[PDB]
Image (cartoon, each protein chain N blue to C red):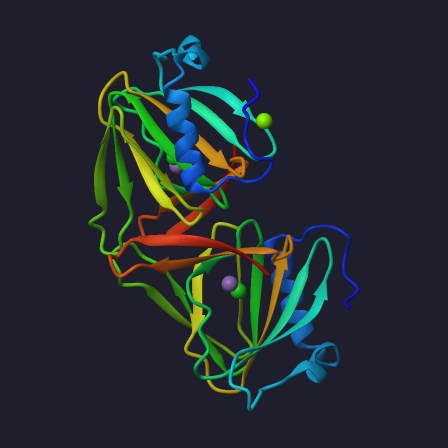
Length: 153
Length: 154
Ligand SMILES: [Cl-]
Ligand SMILES: [Cl-]
Ligand SMILES: [Mg+2]
Ligand SMILES: [Mn+2]
Ligand SMILES: [Mn+2]
């Protein structure tokens, strides 16, 4: 568990949190894992009524798929390696940005994105407030029509 | 007024049955038909409880829902009079459009993204959602073209 405030954090406070956590490897180093399993490894660092914090360790294959975080704001800090964040554009030519170690970003509740194209062994820290208990996963039937499946987390 | 329904969330076909059952019973909704004369569509709640959410809608030719989802709510719609256009979004920008005419009904599961437009002035429709429609996602686009989803509370 982390020792965080007993309230919701806005996106700039989430960004401060993921960046200060990056500078405190004591909070997360023991949770760094890359399975011979295949499959993306998650590690929860903190979950309470206000904030969720995760440590993600990325393989080159990992893809979040398109999704929003319902009512959760969030922030991401890349600790090692690099990620690609994709934002959806009506038309099909999505904007893609590479986020490298040391760099971070934040988003509000209306955000839709996809995190993918990771360097193998990449590590990142993700923080959400309110907690990420629901997320919407966007899919496309081969008829082209998009849907949003709201999933627990 | 109370509705004799299972004490649970209803699937999309049970909602469709419900809206068609209600349509065939004018005694329950004819009272509440009223067509407004500015922007705001006129909504009339026929029944809301812990499982279901039933509305009577009266459309003007302008009325547009905008692109939106219903979060985790399944839904059904029966057009009582007039006609509605149901748009479904496609990647590529060429969205699917379907005219739903008086007497016809459709239903959808909880993953549905659509847009409803009044295709004929004076139209009347009955909508049912389950679970209740407490939050809705309304999609918008920047000039940049990037899509966002604003979770609204109705
Ligand atoms: Cl994220
Ligand atoms: Cl609807
Ligand atoms: Mg009831
Ligand atoms: Mn995300
Ligand atoms: Mn709708």
